[PDB]
Amino acid sequence: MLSRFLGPRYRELARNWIPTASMWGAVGAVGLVWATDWRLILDWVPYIN
Amino acid sequence: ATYAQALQSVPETQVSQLDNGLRVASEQSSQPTCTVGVWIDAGSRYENEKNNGAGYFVEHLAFKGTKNRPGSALEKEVESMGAHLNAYSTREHTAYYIKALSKDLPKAVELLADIVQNCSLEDSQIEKERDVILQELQENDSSMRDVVFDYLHATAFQGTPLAQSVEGPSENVRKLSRADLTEYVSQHYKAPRMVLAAAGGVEHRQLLDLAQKHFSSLSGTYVEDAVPAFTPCRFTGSEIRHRDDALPLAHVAIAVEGPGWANPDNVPLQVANAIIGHYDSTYGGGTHMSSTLASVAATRKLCQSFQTFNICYAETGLLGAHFVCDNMSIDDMMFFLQGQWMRLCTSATESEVVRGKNILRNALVSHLDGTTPVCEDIGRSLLTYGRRIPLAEWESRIAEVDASVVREVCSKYFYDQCPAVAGLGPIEQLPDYNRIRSGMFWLRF
Amino acid sequence: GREFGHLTRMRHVITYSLSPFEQRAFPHYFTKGIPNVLRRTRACILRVAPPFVVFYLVYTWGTQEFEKSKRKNPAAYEN
Amino acid sequence: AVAASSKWLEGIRKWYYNAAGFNKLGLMRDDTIYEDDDVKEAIRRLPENLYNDRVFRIKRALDLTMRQQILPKEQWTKYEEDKFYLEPYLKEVIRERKEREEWAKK
Amino acid sequence: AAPTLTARLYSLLFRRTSTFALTIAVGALFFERAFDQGADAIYEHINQGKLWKHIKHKYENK
Amino acid sequence: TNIRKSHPLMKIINNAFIDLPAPSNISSWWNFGSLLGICLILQILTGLFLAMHYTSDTTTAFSSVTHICRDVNYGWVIRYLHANGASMFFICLFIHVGRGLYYGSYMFLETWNIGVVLLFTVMATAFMGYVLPWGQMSFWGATVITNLLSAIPYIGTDLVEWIWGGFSVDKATLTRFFAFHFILPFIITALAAVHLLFLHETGSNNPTGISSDMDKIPFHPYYTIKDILGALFMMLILLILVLFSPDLLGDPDNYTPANPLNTPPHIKPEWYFLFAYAILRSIPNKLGGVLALVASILILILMPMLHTSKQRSMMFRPLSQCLFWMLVADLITLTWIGGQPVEHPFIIIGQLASILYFLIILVLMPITSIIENNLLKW
Ligand code: HEM
Ligand code: HEM
Ligand SMILES: COC(=O)N(OC)c1ccccc1COc1ccn(-c2ccc(Cl)cc2)n1
């Protein structure tokens, strides 16, 4: 009975908020490896070695 | 039978022009009364610091006697037929108009032409209109709403002609001579800057021949006829605080810079202000009302009233809100109001926009009810757009507004912008300008 | 904001009290107390006790089947 | 809604009323409800004589539990005398909450 | 009234403050490995022929 | 002009302990919250002594503890005050949680959620104190945590190596276990002031489950003298276990020193971890077993969401009282199974009792409250 997500007006709930998050599910693959001392994305580019 | 069919059967406006450039417009509506008047491009934004009380001084002497009808003889003629005379003055317009019977139209046009062309500015009516104006200024100081909107113009347009008041300072009122008033009429009461409008039981052919009989001796082009220079005015983010703890309630006005008259952004910005709304403590709606700021202020008893405004000039304007509350409630009212502006820049829903479009359609047709507001809409639309925009054209602009358009225009005008603030009364809890400026952007979006 | 004068609304209720120095600190102790703690035991015995009986039967079956799976071999111990 | 178990399922209802023991403290069924936001709005809407009856019945039951005692058996609340005084006021408060929720999504 | 080059990417990335919440993570590069130009090339220049990895070819593969 | 109502420091104490409104029918089950505050203070003024005379290394840990019982003056009394004082903390914690589960006190949402954080922090602290004496139970009990901690599929192999001091069993293992044990009891003391500040917004619940704003009494002198009497009865039980049988709660095999010398005859922790060791041991997968260990304590956070009764407490719910005591008898079974060897009858029993612990909380309790709702004609 959490049907507050199920509504015909608040379907645009998720359409004004996900254009923020176009990278925000992968910022751990951009930002945490700045301090992990791993090579997660350090093979992707010839930017860094 | 349909609202769409009823907008087609509205009678149209007919416009003509004389040889001197005077425009003549009418709308015939088959009723025994009429309203006729003269609308002029004159106001306090055309005055400098030496004659800032000049146009408001001239409006006082307009019904005190002309060359043909001296003294009270003008007043006896209007009253003996059962007619009314009125006038006003804003920062950009000036109007004089008559409400009379529709068979008294030739006498009404003749009196209006004698008022604007041959008014006597006699030196004994001056020096006794000074004391009437000086006492009216002291009465204006007791109206807190009029003081706080004069403060908002003086800080948003600081070093421009648009920051002056209509009435002018008290030292100018004490020193305006007879020579300064005759220069004001010769420079500003000119025929391509005037509109003769009429609404009611009028034929357009009859008004045109009355305009040729009484107005044709107006000077068309002028001595040396230089183009009236238009200096624009810039907006400045700033604030002014007047602290007076002895007043019982506090008045606060805040605005950002808005669009001009002919900007097409004006229509979706009025759909947006209709979603915020207005409130007053004598309302019966209260806690059930659709506006979020109105429903919160009624539940918690936060304010006495609020309103949103859309003030337009030729190139700029003011877009904001005004509210009245007690000394313990200023910080909460500013928090909830700024949170509703940011919730329209993002997040604006389609169901809010449908309600806000219905409010704007009802407010447009409710204004045009009677001969006097129809005649005023004719006279100031020809000075502003150069034409009268009919009701069918307003409806097709309103119908193309949706939720994504409102989000784009509100983000352009509100988001991350410097406001202008004015405050009067017990305002110790009015927040700091750095905390107000930080309220115009979010953490997330 | 939860202090004693601001809690709730109450009407038409009267209370009577005695000083502690005017009464005896031990009234009826075994005359009232022993019949009181016995019907309190009767009121809760059918709710609390039957779970702990089933723990006892599982514990006895679990320790006795542990031994005769291990080195207890009477008759299954041939060629 | 079975007509064959009309009396049998009322025997289990009368048994459960006595196994629960708020009637031994002199309480009615609506005295024992958990007070969330819809219940607290229904208490505010009660008439003044039903409010004062509820406040005294709760105070007398809290005083009995402090002493670990119950009432005499002739003063227990009977099963077919229990008045559901709060149930009409609570059904109206909930219907108003569900009306404001269909409006917020349509 | 042509402006200067301070409209950096303000209309492109910086308006909606999506950048500002995660500049510890996303906008974090160009200042460790691009600063090989920094201290280590300066510190070994003041101390040329004095560190161990300067006197190193003299003592291997002998 | 009353100084205890106007002084800035005295008025905080007056609102918290003296003039606080309290329900009049509060039972002895509400005594165990101040008993937990006595046990936490006592474990701080006794852990002072032990960390003073201490050295934590793989060569001297087992002898650094035997030095205190014989050579260090008043060291036998203070060591066994500390080992039995932690058993006293854990019995006062399980009574406390079972009270709030029975009477519906979890409806105070913010107070309940800080409590679940407090239950995790004392459980992890006491695990890192039993590894310090370095006996057989210290070694083989720590080396079954890291088998399920290296089972974390990405970061786990460098996680255990960062907390083992650097390689394996070595000198510096007991410099990170000892660091994670000196400082964790002080996060508990700050989390307890926040825990009471949220309770002060509503006051206390009572055994009837009905609000008691018409029947409040002051906290002094009624519950100040009742909390002092209950604390005196706790010191009697604790000093009896210290001065008459100081090794009753313990294992003799942790007096045999630590070495990878030989496999022990058994592996078992202290009594207050035996319910948790029995659950993970009945899962034949070192990732499924570490998930059901954390899911046996963090399942308490779902108790506000799973509530379907119209009443708050269990005083008037006879069908729900039967299920509450089936859950207590299920945790007694897991404490017994967790000290048994892994043989034939103790695997089918220890894994069916692991299932029934989750079936009661998630499925059987929400359905039974709905059945009782229908029987009372709501
Ligand atoms: C170091 C650990 C703890 C300390 C010092 C502590 C302290 C206290 C104190 C003093 C009280 C008020 C008196 C009382 O009702 O007993 C209390 C109440 C409460 N505690 Fe704790 N507690 C601790 C752990 C926990 C845990 C583990 C939980 C739950 C998971 C919890 C949940 C609650 C709740 C819900 C209440 C209010 C109960 C009611 O009023 O009915 N606490 N606590
Ligand atoms: C919540 C509080 C505490 C708990 C539950 C706790 C628990 C324990 C346990 C289970 C032991 C093992 C005793 C044994 O097996 O013989 C122990 C000992 C030890 N504790 Fe604590 N303790 C607490 C507080 C503290 C504090 C405050 C300190 C340090 C100031 C500390 C430091 C130590 C040390 C160094 C030992 C090793 C000495 C020994 O084993 O006798 N502990 N504690
Ligand atoms: C007093 O210490 C012992 O009993 N320890 O550890 C030295 C021991 C000794 C021998 C065998 C096993 C253990 C530990 O067994 C368990 C089982 C579950 N936990 C646990 C620990 C922390 C947290 Cl947060 C949650 C669960 N620990």
Image: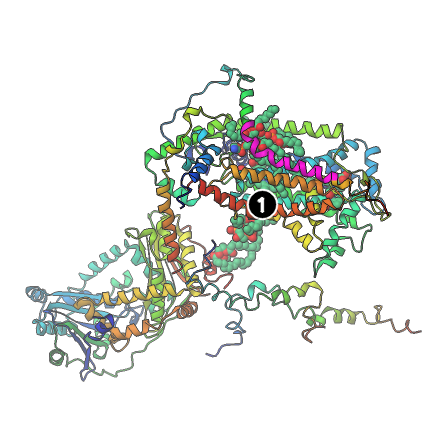
Tell me if I can see residue B312 in this picture. yes
Task: Tell me residue D29's x, y (percent).
Answer: 42, 36
Query: Relative to F94, does residue B235 appear above or below in the rendering?
Result: below
Q: Chain of mark 1?
A: F
Residue located at (38% from left, 31% from top): C10
Residue F148: where, in percent of width, then height? 72, 54
Residue C49 belongs to the span the image colors magenta: yes
Location of residue F69 with respect to F198 vertically, above or below:
above
| Magenta segment | C41-64
Say what amino acid the circle numbered 1 marks.
Answer: Ile
Can residue E52 be found in the magenta stretch?
A: no
* Image position of F225 (left or right of C77): left
Q: Nearer the viewer, residue B400 or F9?
A: B400
Q: Which residue is mark 1?
A: F360
**Residue F35 seen by the camera:** no
Occupied quadrant, residue B406: bottom left
Q: For the stretch drawn in magenta, what is the main secondary structure?
A: helix
Which residue is more in the foreground, F40 or F332?
F332
